[PDB]
Image 1 (cartoon, rainbow, N blue to C red):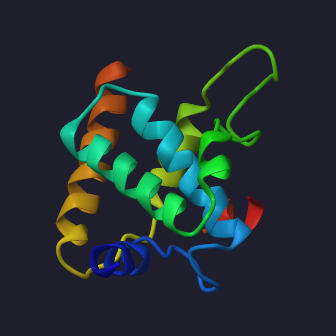
Image 2 (cartoon, helix red, strand yellow; image 1 turned 135 degrees about the horizontal axis):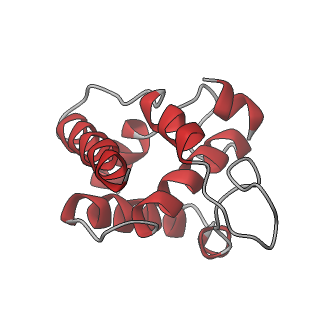
Length: 127
């Protein structure tokens, strides 16, 4: 209860709440991203914590119905990952300042941007 209330207010990313369809849309890309890349310790901590939070609020089926959204594919069957738009999504992610999730969120964002470099706002209003 205590640490989940802290983590829900740490990943609001919107105005309505942690249960709104816009926040559930923007969390979907982060859960897809975490598993969509190399299994990091910070990435799997963020994944398990979002999973615990969606179990608590009664949205576990909506967690297990996650995939990449339609605003990151080029074709439905041809699984293509629009990395430039995804980098714009991660770069425009309003990560909060409250400890201890600000440091972890910032390091998560840095290693995701760094790993997509090593391979080579409007988003939440859309989804």
